[PDB]
Length: 461
Ligand SMILES: Cc1nsc(N(C)CC(N)=O)c1C#N
Ligand SMILES: Cc1nsc(N(C)CC(N)=O)c1C#N
Ligand SMILES: [Zn+2]
Ligand SMILES: [Zn+2]
Ligand SMILES: [Zn+2]
Image 1 (spheres, rainbow, N blue to C red):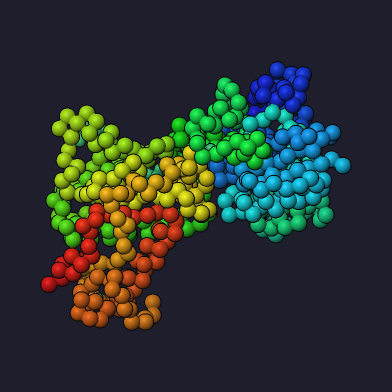
Image 2: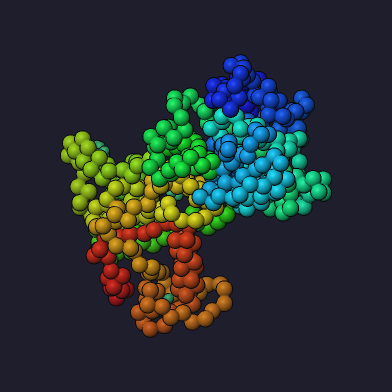
């Protein structure tokens, strides 16, 4: 019960316009054969081209929407569309490209998938709303066989060259002409009524149809992400490390302690309302304040309405207007003015951030968190939190070479007294590095308007 059995049934109703007469009774085994491939009863780690929803979900970083449309099968030119927004035209003889034979079109397909996937995944998962021409066009740019390794490294092979008779991973595939052991999944097997557009458009206003292949390709992956990460959410699934996940997570813990510790020292709030992750611990355990926790899961769909988060069954609702509210990745429509806020900017370009549904994004760092579209209007009662470092810790090296530090934002006893000590200079530069890691990773920080670092200087006297 791990891999999809080739003897599992495939519903063929979706195929019967491109492929009139298709059997109603069809397995993957007979489908794969009809697509022109031979699985030669092989136990070499590639039991099926098609995969389970669960396997697709574990390999979300690999998803590429794929769609083909008749343009004017062997007779006529095909439009090949990918969720990268690329459209190629193959002949048998937003980016749109002119008609070319399969022998060159297939080279472009390897280049495009390699550049897209090399920093994301060991594989490709073609995500389909299958009507026939996509499945019957794969023989023109795919080869299958036993699992294999790169000729230049230890990564599993994803490409093949007919020039050299060799195999490559995504990193090493320059000049390769065939996709090797792709995976794929037909969204239409999941139990949907009506066409792609009419299902996509229930959930997403951001992707339009121009009746071109890359738009269906984009809409297909959008609808898949909706089904697997918005309506359904499995926070048990771990995902591999592929970048700065560990540094970014550590940065986030450091900045949070810094910012909340400072907020308490500056304005001496008697109560902090900690709204979000129900696992959460006091980020400033030594602080003087009444720490009151409030449970809420990541909203993956729409931002929480502050009205419904606080004052539903307001049967003596807690005084959320007293003290300060901490929303650490707890997304609401409009934050109260007495708030400290970390909010992920869905618009960021990174290897951890994949395009999502209805202007939102899928942030994959240890877990997958689909995140509602970033909206500036959420922050109207707040301001951007300016950078600063604060320490009450004694000046004392205990031991990373030095250039004497000058900064207006180094809030320490030493800088008050004129000259930053070596210890606080190291800590300052380390904290600035963490802070920049975090920001570039896409997190944005916002605070109550009365917040002023000038108030921190009187905590040394
Ligand atoms: C008493 C109580 N039950 S529910 C609740 N909140 C804040 C959540 C909500 N949805 O209103 C409170 C409080 N305080
Ligand atoms: C890294 C992280 N920790 S919890 C979280 N949430 C609540 C997801 C969200 N929907 O905003 C994020 C993000 N991003
Ligand atoms: Zn390699
Ligand atoms: Zn969409
Ligand atoms: Zn110092």
